[PDB]
Amino acid sequence: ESWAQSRDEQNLLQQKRIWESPLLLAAKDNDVQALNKLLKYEDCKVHQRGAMGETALHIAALYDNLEAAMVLMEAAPELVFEPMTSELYEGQTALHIAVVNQNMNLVRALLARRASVSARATGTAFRRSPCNLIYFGEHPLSFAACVNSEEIVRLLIEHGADIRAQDSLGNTVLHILILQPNKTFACQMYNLLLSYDRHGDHLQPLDLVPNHQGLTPFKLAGVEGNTVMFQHLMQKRKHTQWTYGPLTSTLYDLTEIDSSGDEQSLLELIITTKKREARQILDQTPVKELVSLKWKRYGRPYFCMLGAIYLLYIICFTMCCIYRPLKPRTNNRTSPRDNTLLQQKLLQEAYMTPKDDIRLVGELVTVIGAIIILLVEVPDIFRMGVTRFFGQTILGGPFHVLIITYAFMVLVTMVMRLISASGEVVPMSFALVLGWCNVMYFARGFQMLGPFTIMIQKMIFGDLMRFCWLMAVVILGFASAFYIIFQTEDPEELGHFYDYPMALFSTFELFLTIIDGPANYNVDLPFMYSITYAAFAIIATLLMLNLLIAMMGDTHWRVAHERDELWRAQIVATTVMLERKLPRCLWPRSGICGREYGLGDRWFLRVED
Amino acid sequence: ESWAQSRDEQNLLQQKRIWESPLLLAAKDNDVQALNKLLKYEDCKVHQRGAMGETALHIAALYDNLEAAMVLMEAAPELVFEPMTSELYEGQTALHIAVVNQNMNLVRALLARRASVSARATGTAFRRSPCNLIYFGEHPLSFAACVNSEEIVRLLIEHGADIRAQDSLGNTVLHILILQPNKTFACQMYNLLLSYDRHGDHLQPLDLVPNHQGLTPFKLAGVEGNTVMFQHLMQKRKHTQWTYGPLTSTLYDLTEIDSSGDEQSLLELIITTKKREARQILDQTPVKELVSLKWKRYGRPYFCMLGAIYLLYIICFTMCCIYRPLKPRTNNRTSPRDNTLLQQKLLQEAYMTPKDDIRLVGELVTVIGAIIILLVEVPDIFRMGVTRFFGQTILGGPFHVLIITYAFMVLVTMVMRLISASGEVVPMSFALVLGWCNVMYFARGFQMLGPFTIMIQKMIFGDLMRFCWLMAVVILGFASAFYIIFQTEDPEELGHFYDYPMALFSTFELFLTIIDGPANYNVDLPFMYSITYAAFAIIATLLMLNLLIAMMGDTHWRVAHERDELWRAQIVATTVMLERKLPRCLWPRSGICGREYGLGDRWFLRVED
Ligand SMILES: CCCCCCCC/C=C\CCCCCCCC(=O)O[C@@H](COC(=O)CCCCCCCCCCCCCCC)COP(=O)([O-])OCC[N+](C)(C)C
Ligand SMILES: CCCCCCCC/C=C\CCCCCCCC(=O)O[C@@H](COC(=O)CCCCCCCCCCCCCCC)COP(=O)([O-])OCC[N+](C)(C)C
Ligand SMILES: CC(C)CCC[C@@H](C)[C@H]1CC[C@H]2[C@@H]3CC=C4C[C@@H](OC(=O)CCC(=O)O)CC[C@]4(C)[C@H]3CC[C@]12C
Ligand SMILES: CC(C)CCC[C@@H](C)[C@H]1CC[C@H]2[C@@H]3CC=C4C[C@@H](OC(=O)CCC(=O)O)CC[C@]4(C)[C@H]3CC[C@]12C
Ligand SMILES: CC(C)CCC[C@@H](C)[C@H]1CC[C@H]2[C@@H]3CC=C4C[C@@H](OC(=O)CCC(=O)O)CC[C@]4(C)[C@H]3CC[C@]12C
Ligand SMILES: CC(C)CCC[C@@H](C)[C@H]1CC[C@H]2[C@@H]3CC=C4C[C@@H](OC(=O)CCC(=O)O)CC[C@]4(C)[C@H]3CC[C@]12C
Ligand SMILES: CC(C)CCC[C@@H](C)[C@H]1CC[C@H]2[C@@H]3CC=C4C[C@@H](OC(=O)CCC(=O)O)CC[C@]4(C)[C@H]3CC[C@]12C
Ligand SMILES: CC(C)CCC[C@@H](C)[C@H]1CC[C@H]2[C@@H]3CC=C4C[C@@H](OC(=O)CCC(=O)O)CC[C@]4(C)[C@H]3CC[C@]12C
Ligand SMILES: Clc1ccc(CO[C@@H](Cn2ccnc2)c2ccc(Cl)cc2Cl)cc1
Ligand SMILES: Clc1ccc(CO[C@@H](Cn2ccnc2)c2ccc(Cl)cc2Cl)cc1
């Protein structure tokens, strides 16, 4: 908004300063005879700074004027050593500009005049931002690699441009190629820049240098969803054992792919990222066979065993609420609308029979199981982001909130049982609902229920929320109308709208048609009731069929191919989680280690095809 | 109907008069030896007028007879100065006909005989009508431009045909090209006719001359939805600042596009028009970035702020109806069907406690807010069309009617409160429903609810109306059958159909299944009831599933791509409305003005691409 307005004013201010400067105007439209006469007058301000700190050589490079750029260079060679000075294009020399324009006659002329090939374009328009259309890095090698200029990238390296140079983000030129929109040119420019890594004395290969986030180019291809660069980079990690007719046994390196646990791996990065195209990497041929085999061998048995424990635990909590201690009430009824018969016992009376001691066993099992949930969920999100990266795992998984909220409602029921507080049915009823609805976390391990259950998550976070905002507006209008229509009437015949919170709840139930329409037929109802309830019935039939259309076309050709891809992504997210919190004796590491096969200390996945 | 019948009889009358005239028949089938002998006899009626005022040169031009047309011209040259005289083809000379047929040998022969290139074909078959298949303008330059004849348009201009000539609609030849079905030939014929605007002494360029509606050719391309002519015309208004590799900074003129407020602009014309293809112009690259930036910067905050005020106002009106003054009834009940307990107070008793004065604050806030609605909606539609162009904005927006009807129902409740009239629940109940259902006007500002809420409008104005006409027919048959089946029975057991207005309302509720089927089981019902209610239940299950099919296929591949385009069109209609009624201090004008950048007094939108 405001900064994009400020960029627009500086770009218009650039064009004004070109027109009102006879030096800069001459370089824009290649009037070399105008370049002569301003130098015939005096050896004047070639140190004219424009709006973005332009010099006239920067103007001649931007508008692709060869002959205009020459006259600046013989008259003042020092303008090749000058960068732009403004905050928007800081550090950019005319070497950067001639490379991006692919003006090769100009960039040969600049390298003849020792133009600095290590100049860092550190301006704001060169950062990797949502508000910059290019991210070319900041070195002229990085700018040449992104414009697909195989001649200039050779020309700069043969004049001393360093292929080891990083940016403020730490991205080397191999990282920057992965961030490029034309992914096929990036593969050709990958191999050429990797070919100049002849040096076996630079301590580390170029494809193994991490950026400041600690990602290598291989791992950065997985995070960005760059499936084209991912398949290309993986062929360096293949090793074909044999070829038997149509058969081919291929051996995969599985080093940065597999979750080793010391550093964040390629499986962990893809699960925790916001790119939709990173999920496409899970179907690639090292990663697909890797995570499907550790699911079938070890992930799925340790998930169904972990669901059978949660099922027996939630039956144990359920029985402790069915058999909760209750005694007949003491006082008399305050009013004839008082429905209550029983009340909960105090702590002294709650354990005075042998049936109360079998319950006390299950209540302690419930308390312990709720603490263990808080011992494994509450600390392990503090080492992550407390609310933000936790909340980014809520859009990935809502069952983080639901089982923490379950375990809190249980310990609230414990504290209310200790201090003998009235109203234990409130935290119990939240916990029975939350604790049972957490069983459909375990629907993802079953191939029948798994894809069905993600479609729940898409429609609660989507279309059912769109419906409920417009439902609550219609309810607030009609519950208020139904309240005042029956505000004069006797409530002993038709009590649906007797006060305003019940009128509001009756209209919600009439909207969903889960209670019948109010009718007596023995008494006269207001005529305004039938007019209003007819209009209410049409608007509800409109909305509840609008939802059924909206839930439809969003979920047949839009997310039906996505729900099965997100089910396979939940298998990976479940397996990465179960491998992380279980010890190595329970989880044998995937692949086959070397060192007894001559392959090293790396772990290999053999895929026969 | 009648006039299309009259056109058909004149076209058959033309062919009869050709056959029974030996002059006109000879020119139709190119019998030049028959043309000789009628002139050998006498210098006879070459002034023969046919049915549409044809002469024989008009016949020879219509049937593409070169050699037949020559014999008319040497024998009588004055027939090139004659137009057709009938009302259907008035003004049409043989110059018009030879141009439309692209008979270039004939039109060179006519221009050799000083044929009038400024002749106005003002006949009814040349007007822009739904009942004419061509709109070619009315000058021979306009006819040449529409048949794609680049040779004849040069030939007429080099004989003196004026490119500044307008029609009865005021359309110059550049306007007429935009109205043409082959839009790609129109772009080539645009540039050629714009090339002959060498004259810098004709006070105004050809692309800047308005028609009688005040539209220029650029604005007429937006109104007609001519997206091909729109992109072509916009390239005259671009200005490329620089080109940096793949980047390009383009500067857009934004003069006739942006709502300046003095004259109707291109954004205002497209919103208020009935063409569906004009909505395609909103996705074009000056217009899309313009209206998305003024929505995100200024349109959406002033719309959510304006919805938060309407939400607090409608809660204030709601509480003033919940706490409406009511007293216990005075008289005794007229009958045991009288349900009423309370009645509304008179004006004297209505304000006699401190709780009635807090309500009086909110009641005055309600009265003032209803007048302000009538001060900003009722005058500003009178300056528009009172009912017609107002009603054309009802098919655009139904919330014009709904918030005017709300504000009327509030002031009716005020007048009923003043004169102390019984029955204030009737205008209150309409106003609670209307006032709350106007909150989903503000669903369009939210990207989640916006596309959902237009699908409400498509289905109430569409499929739910188709259902309700056929519902009311089925209800009127079965409520009448259910009335007479229980007409003999005792109503104290089953009172659903006790009189005819309740039988009609019960059948409506039984149709929508919002009340249960009438049953007693303690008494014998008529056997005709079970037969009828079974047939009623099948026909309702037929219809309510027919609707669910009809609401489906009309709204998945038919309007699902249209509902999102109509949501973006509502953003534009909301933004044009909010810019129009808010002052310039609240709304900073979009773009960047010139005059401090050497660009003039125009306002420019920079788009980097
Ligand atoms: C996904 C959806 C989420 C939203 C859920 C919201 C759904 C609704 C949930 C909650 C809303 C209701 C809360 C209060 C209800 C009871 C309060 C009460 O005690 O009653 C008192 C006040 O009664 C009133 O009339 C004041 C409340 C006006 C309702 C306006 C909505 C407020 C929120 C707007 C939000 C906009 C939402 C739409 C967005 C634009 C009076 O009632 P009584 O006891 O009968 O006394 C009669 C007087 N007598 C004593 C003289 C006899
Ligand atoms: C989107 C849909 C829009 C249309 C909505 C329409 C839906 C319906 C809405 C309104 C229609 C009903 C209006 C009158 C109802 C009550 C009148 C009354 O006082 O009752 C009296 C007359 O009762 C009758 O039988 C006469 C009315 C016959 C109904 C024919 C339809 C009229 C409109 C056709 C339009 C066609 C529509 C389809 C298009 C082709 C008698 O009733 P009673 O009190 O029981 O007295 C018993 C006699 N006793 C005293 C001897 C005991
Ligand atoms: C007295 C004792 C024996 C009671 C028994 C306790 C178990 C039934 C509890 C204790 C810890 C629980 C586990 C703690 C952590 C998790 C992770 C949790 O993961 C998510 O919900 C992730 C969210 C998402 O990705 O959607 C699923 C339940 C599970 C396996 C829990 C399953 C039930 C467990 C084993
Ligand atoms: C005692 C009552 C008042 C409890 C209060 C209601 C809410 C606190 C709870 C009750 C049931 C819960 C829901 C039960 C089931 C689901 C489905 C669940 O969807 C999935 O299974 C995710 C997709 C997948 O992993 O396959 C998302 C959470 C949600 C909506 C839960 C959200 C929180 C809810 C509404
Ligand atoms: C997003 C989904 C889960 C719900 C969609 C709308 C809800 C936010 C609203 C709409 C109608 C509301 C209900 C309508 C009115 C009432 C009565 C209200 O009254 C009371 O406090 C006591 C019970 C009574 O008197 O009815 C209690 C909340 C409740 C059930 C409301 C709970 C919240 C609801 C479901
Ligand atoms: C005592 C006072 C402070 C009461 C508060 C009054 C406001 C709540 C009212 C007064 C004027 C109203 C506005 C008058 C005009 C309009 C235009 C109206 O536009 C349409 O409905 C267009 C129809 C369509 O395009 O569908 C939407 C509501 C709105 C913003 C109204 C919103 C509510 C406002 C600000
Ligand atoms: C007290 C009772 C008897 C009131 C009488 C009923 C009608 C006078 C009112 C009640 C609710 C109104 C409806 C409430 C909501 C809508 C949705 C609305 O659709 C939109 O939101 C338009 C699309 C968009 O702009 O996104 C169109 C009008 C309509 C059908 C209204 C039409 C007029 C209705 C039926
Ligand atoms: C287009 C949508 C909004 C409605 C679809 C059909 C309506 C035009 C008709 C069909 C059935 C009609 C209802 C059926 C019968 C009655 C009873 C009638 O009786 C009375 O006057 C008092 C109440 C009673 O005795 O039932 C009042 C109107 C009402 C509700 C009618 C209102 C108009 C309705 C909804
Ligand atoms: Cl919400 C929900 C989530 C998970 C399950 C597990 O359901 C198990 C059945 N099962 C086994 C022991 N107790 C129940 C199951 C379901 C389907 C198939 Cl095809 C196969 C199996 Cl084994 C059930 C409901
Ligand atoms: Cl019919 C209808 C029309 C408009 C709204 C506005 O709803 C707001 C919520 N809100 C804020 C204050 N009071 C309610 C909202 C809805 C959805 C999303 Cl994604 C985001 C927001 Cl902020 C609600 C119902």
Image (cartoon, coloured by chain):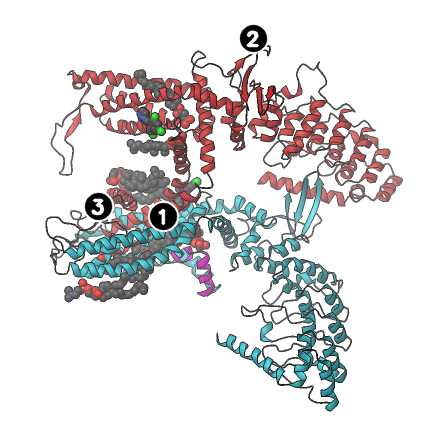
Chain colours: A red, B cyan
Query: For this rendering, which residue is in front, B457 or B380?
Result: B457
The answer to whether residue B571 shows anywhere in this view is: yes
Residue corresponding to mark 1: A545
Q: Image quadrant of ligand 4? A: top left
Query: For this rendering, which residue is in front, B594 or A485?
Result: A485
User: Magenta stretch: dominant SS?
Assistant: helix
Q: Earlier in the sequence, mark 3 or mark 2?
A: 3
Residue corresponding to mark 2: A596
Q: Earlier in the sequence, mark 2 or mark 1?
A: 1
CA–CA distance between discs 3 and 2? 82 Å
The answer to whether residue B367 shows anywhere in this view is: no
Amino acid bearing label 2: Glu
Q: Residue farthest to the front?
A: A245
| Residues packed near mark 1 inside 10 Å, few (<14), some (14 to 19) or many (20 plus) | some
Depth check, mark 3 against mark 1: the one in front is 1
Q: Position of residue A251 (x, y in %)?
A: 57, 19
Helix, strand or loop under label 3: loop
Specify the quadrant that holds the C terminus of chain A: top right
Q: Position of residue B266 (x, y in %)?
A: 58, 56
Which of the 4 quarters of the picture holds residue B159? Answer: bottom right
Residue corresponding to mark 3: A498
Depth check, mark 2 against mark 1: the one in front is 2
Magenta segment boundaries in residue numbering: B387-403
Amino acid bearing label 1: Leu
Note whether B602 is above or below A608 in the view shown. below
CA–CA distance between discs 2 and 1? 66 Å
